[PDB]
Amino acid sequence: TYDIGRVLGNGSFGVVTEARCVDTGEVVAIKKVLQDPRKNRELDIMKELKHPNVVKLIDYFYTEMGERDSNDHNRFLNVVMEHIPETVYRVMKSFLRANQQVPFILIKLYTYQMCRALGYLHALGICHRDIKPQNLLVDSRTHVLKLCDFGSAKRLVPGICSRFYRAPELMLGASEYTTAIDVWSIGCVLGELLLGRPLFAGETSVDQLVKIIQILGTPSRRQMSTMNPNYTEFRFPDVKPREWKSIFASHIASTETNDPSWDQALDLLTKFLRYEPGERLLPLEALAHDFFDELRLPSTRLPSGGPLPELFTFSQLELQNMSPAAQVKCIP
Amino acid sequence: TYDIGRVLGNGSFGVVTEARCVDTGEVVAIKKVLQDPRYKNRELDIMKELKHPNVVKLIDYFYTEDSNDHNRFLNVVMEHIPETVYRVMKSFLRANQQVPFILIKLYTYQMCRALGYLHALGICHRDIKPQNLLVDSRTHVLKLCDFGSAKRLVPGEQYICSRFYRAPELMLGASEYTTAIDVWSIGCVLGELLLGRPLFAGETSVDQLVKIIQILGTPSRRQMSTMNPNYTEFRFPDVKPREWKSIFASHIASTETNDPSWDQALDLLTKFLRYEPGERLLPLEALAHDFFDELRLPSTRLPSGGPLPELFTFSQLELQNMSPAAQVKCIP
Amino acid sequence: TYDIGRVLGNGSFGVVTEARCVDTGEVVAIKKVLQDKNRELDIMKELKHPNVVKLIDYFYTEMGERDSNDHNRFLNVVMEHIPETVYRVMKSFLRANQQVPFILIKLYTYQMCRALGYLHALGICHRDIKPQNLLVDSRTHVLKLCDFGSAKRLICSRFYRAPELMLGASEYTTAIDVWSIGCVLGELLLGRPLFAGETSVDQLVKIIQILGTPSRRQMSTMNPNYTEFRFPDVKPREWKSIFASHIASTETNDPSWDQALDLLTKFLRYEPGERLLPLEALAHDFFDELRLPSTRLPSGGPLPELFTFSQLELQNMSPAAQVKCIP
Amino acid sequence: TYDIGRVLGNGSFGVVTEARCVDTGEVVAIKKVLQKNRELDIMKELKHPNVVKLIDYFYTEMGERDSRFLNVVMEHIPETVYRVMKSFLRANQQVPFILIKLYTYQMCRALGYLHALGICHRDIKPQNLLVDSRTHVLKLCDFGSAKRLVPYICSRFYRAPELMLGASEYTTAIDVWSIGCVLGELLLGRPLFAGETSVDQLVKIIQILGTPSRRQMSTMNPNYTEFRFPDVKPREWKSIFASHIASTETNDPSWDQALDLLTKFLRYEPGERLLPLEALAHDFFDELRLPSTRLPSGGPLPELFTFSQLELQNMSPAAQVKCIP
Ligand SMILES: O=C1NC(=O)C(c2cnc3ccccn23)=C1c1cn2c3c(cc(F)cc13)CN(C(=O)N1CCCCC1)CC2
Ligand SMILES: O=C1NC(=O)C(c2cnc3ccccn23)=C1c1cn2c3c(cc(F)cc13)CN(C(=O)N1CCCCC1)CC2
Ligand SMILES: O=C1NC(=O)C(c2cnc3ccccn23)=C1c1cn2c3c(cc(F)cc13)CN(C(=O)N1CCCCC1)CC2
Ligand SMILES: O=C1NC(=O)C(c2cnc3ccccn23)=C1c1cn2c3c(cc(F)cc13)CN(C(=O)N1CCCCC1)CC2
């Protein structure tokens, strides 16, 4: 049913390629992975998701190979998905090359839809576990953002690489963690969208723990125990917490032009990037932040002038995972 | 001119699959990786250079069959060896049996010699682990492979997700290192061969440094900085150095007639696993160690009874990169 | 003693698995069969030959009680491990749309004959020779017999079974293994089974369509209960007809095609008594290439063991065969 | 959940072993196969008085290395028709007619059920027909060869003639032919067409059914038309059992009804072989429908008549009034 043509980089190690569905002429994305045919976690998770900001699962099928053999005729699972041409990663580097900041309306739209998508996932009990700009699909014309790449997602049963966006509890080898690790990533994406470069760029985990400490300050004994208990008494150098207003001072200087956006973005950044995972602002709660107040005004449009994408038709599971204060605030 | 059938696994990015050469009837391994024909492939150029009894032979290579494409598929054809040190180890583990000292000697020797040659060309493998060490049970030949991470370390430049066998300088944001990182791996493999489990098994960059310190002791201020200068004044908790006979006490206990095997292996383990990369015993130099004296006796055989594999017909390049003291000891 | 791992497949009446010998690190095959004395193990203890699997060890494993139930007892036969079969090598070339090179057809057929000649010299009949039983190492191109669950001093296969067996014969000779040798030479040259019928009737017809009608007397040397039994009358075809297309595609100014087919005709004969004996076959011109000193594997390597005949092998070779076979 | 113990033998593939369910103490049979299965998928569909119940299934791993066992758990019954047969054979005695009727009936009803789901068993033989000596219940088992036949195993004596001619395509009638061979052996004390090979067997079939016509031959395998086969005359079933009919006599139509039922089963043309659910209404089973009939033990007869809706749907109207007592 599909013409496979041209490789779109690499997903969860498996290969992702462009494809045309011959019945409709439409282009789709096909991630082919090597499964053992006697159960694939990513595809079972994909079958559950339905949300305005998650890639649609379209079809799936196994490659034939034909060559039988009393060893392993391998077999390849083909997951067919909605094709969206860009990522938040690309839009950023496009603005970077232009030495220009992403407009605050796009930063608001992207962070919102990322938060809403990750809240749904967490409401189903699913943790994406590898949120980074390279996974946040974007449509330049409608500025829809969709989640994708669920090769690392998992239903965290009580009892991954890409290092710039991992939660600090992960870099300390926490043997147990919560869905909050995605919230730390949300903070890192929002952070990079505002800064023009990663907030905590470091080659290894040691290198990053330092850079996080050089900003959040030295973690307390109690904070350290909420991340990894085995390190409750592991002492770090005593660094005093630096504050966002300072790090972005130059950006606030050059850009800022009659906007409280910078105050709201940095406040929202603070509520995401917290050592104690339980103290991190939950994603569906975050939708109510004043940073998104612009998106609920009726006269707000895309910079193009076109209409805003889907933002407000919350499902009941979305509403159920919102505090009463949040439920009143989000109604546009 | 190959019948491609059955996937062996995932190498550096690409997939490796078994294949039959239709001209000779022989079985080979084909690693298919996603190249860009407009650029150069590092792994293939490196392999094109290697000729050594303990490196996989490069047999052939070819590209497999629009604008906006660019992404083509490089097919590298190599010698097929059906096992790894990884598989042999987990084999003995299940039997609650220690790998015999004759094999621990054979494998570590051939690994050192393969890595000594590699260094003599200026190449660094950068990801030595049991899974890369091909083994043939019948001859107990060991060969290096998986050169997707190899590189001719050029002073002045700058990310691997292999966890247990990386050198401490790598787990700090080093950005400059030497071929000594391969020697640290040699130590971890020899360590695991003797212990039945990884010497420093911890899931993250941070957890492992901790596990290494609980054994090697806290690094001195100068030992740090020969690893990563950016962390010279970084103090760790004060751990006392453990004794290898302590870690191996139970293994040393069970195996009666300790002989110098345990003493020579632990002396050789000590000379590999050193914080300062510059103080680590060089791989060809290691060949002359007393641990391998059994390999040089004329009456020594494999446990099967068969003859020992290639061990001593050193090339001229090997000799030039051996201290004169080592050469008289190594040539039997 | 042994670490048991991968299941390689199914032998005669049991499962065969990979295993590591803990003393040596070597990989071996263990055939575990239900000992509910074995014949196969007695047969295995006798065999020593370059082209038979080595018997390495054996031990019993029991599950349950005894006088209570019937518990279980299992014979575990430990053998030399070879990683491929002729069956696998064949299907590999088939997928490639390629003929097995004549040097490998020579090597495999030669070594198969020698093992079966030795086996027969002991008076043993293998009784189930097929590509799945002919172990091969691509690296050396050594061929070894295995799977002796049917061997016997005088089956569920059908494609490589002799015509006498498929006629229900009660008595047979060791020449049933020579028919199987030819059906393997045939598949190596045709790229597909010479006689491939699902059943034990469909198969005789496909044989008849090539060998012609067995004479009144020929049918009597196969199964006497069928002498005066008439079959449809087909005229015998010629192997050069059946292989005409292959002989064209593979061309060459070599006598291999003529020599290979001359050997096929001498193997595949209705009369068991007229079939070329396995050790006599070694002297056939087909294997003259193997006796040249300059010959190598296609790889470039040395040829496997081919000529160091034991004294028993020599006793079962005609004097003409002895001068032709010693290089 | 299970203690795996004594090995009972080999089914279509894999080994079957005795086992105890630790929860109930009950004994069950576990078929362990090396694996979406077909046999397990088919087993999951069947629920009928004369098919083994599938109780459970579970997989064991054993290994964890780069480059599985299905365990099918079933109702345990300690005998087969095969084992009951050798019992009377060794006893120099014929299987009682009430038992022949019971076994053939339950077998027909089980295969009739199986066909109504579109499944073909393809390897019915005495060794597959479980029996309980106490109740004389018969249940089908060993579905490793079953398949639904959307248009290669070594079963010998009970294969249909179209199968022994390797017919690339066939119908569920092959199970009907086996029913006939099982009934036949129950009456004769030995296989009807026992031969070392297929050749020996067609020869034995030809010596009884006579030489097949071209069109009969074309309903089996279109190939081999007008090809081979001497002129052999059809023999008579009453001749074959003449010695048995003497010794027994009985003054009963049992021998006539059995041989009539044998004739309607063992026919070259597959479409002309008596369908199984039809077979239940045959006069042979009239005794099983009498209220005063009991087992030879004195006990009650097993389940025989409480037909599901599908069983009724595949019975001719004449058959339904004949079968309901
Ligand atoms: O349309 C889609 N539906 C999906 O599910 C899906 C998908 C599936 N797995 C992953 C993993 C990461 C990112 C996206 N995906 C795509 C899909 C859409 N592009 C992709 C690209 C590579 C790729 F591999 C998959 C996709 C290239 N590209 C991109 O911007 N990149 C790739 C990595 C570096 C920069 C960020 C532009 C569009
Ligand atoms: O025969 C060969 N010639 C080569 O060049 C080569 C090769 C190329 N890249 C790599 C990376 C790692 C190891 C080997 N290779 C192989 C090659 C040989 N086996 C391989 C296996 C997987 C694979 F993907 C490649 C190969 C499985 N296996 C094995 O023990 N494993 C795989 C990883 C976990 C356990 C260790 C058995 C032999
Ligand atoms: O190493 C060995 N030493 C022995 O004695 C021996 C052995 C014992 N019984 C039999 C029966 C048939 C073939 C070989 N054997 C083996 C042995 C070696 N492989 C085996 C395979 C299955 C198996 F079941 C046994 C073995 C798989 N395979 C293979 O190519 N196949 C299996 C059947 C279909 C295709 C042909 C690759 C290697
Ligand atoms: O209790 C059960 N529930 C099932 O499903 C089932 C079963 C599963 N597969 C097959 C295949 C053939 C026959 C029965 N089965 C049994 C089961 C019950 N016996 C079995 C015997 C062997 C065996 F392997 C399985 C079973 C021995 N025996 C028997 O009379 N034999 C065995 C073959 C030669 C003579 C006939 C008496 C009881």
Image (cartoon, coloured by chain):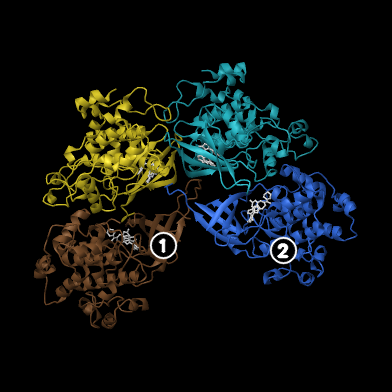
Chain colours: A brown, B yellow, C cyan, D blue
Identify the secondary structure beneath mark 1.
helix
Q: In this view of the protein, which residue sits in the foreground, D178 or B151?
A: D178
| Residue C155, quarter of picture | top right
For disc 1, the chain is A
| Residue D307, quarter of picture | bottom right
Q: In this view of the protein, which residue sits in the foreground, C212 or B183?
A: B183
Q: In this view of the protein, which residue sits in the foreground, C222 or A308?
A: C222
> Neighbour class for label 1 at 10 Å: few (<14), some, many (≥20)?
some
Residue at left offset 27%, top offset 36%: B266
Residue at left offset 41%, top offset 62%: A43
Under mark 2, the amino acid is Arg
Give the side of residue C182 with respect to residue C170, left or right. Answer: left
For the question of whether residue C128 can be seen, the reply is yes
Q: Are the residues at dot 2 and dot 1 in contact (C-beta closer than 8 Å)? A: no
- Report x, y in % for residue D113: 68, 64
Query: Do callouts 2 and 1 point to residues on the same chain?
Result: no
| Residue corresponding to mark 2 | D109
- Report x, y in % for residue A102: 19, 68
Under mark 1, the amino acid is Leu
For the question of whether residue A89 can be seen, the reply is no
Identify the secondary structure beneath mark 2.
helix
- Report x, y in % for residue C109: 55, 30
| Residue corresponding to mark 1 | A43
For disc 2, the chain is D
Give the side of residue A65 with respect to residue C47, left or right. Answer: left
Quadrant containing ligand 1: bottom left
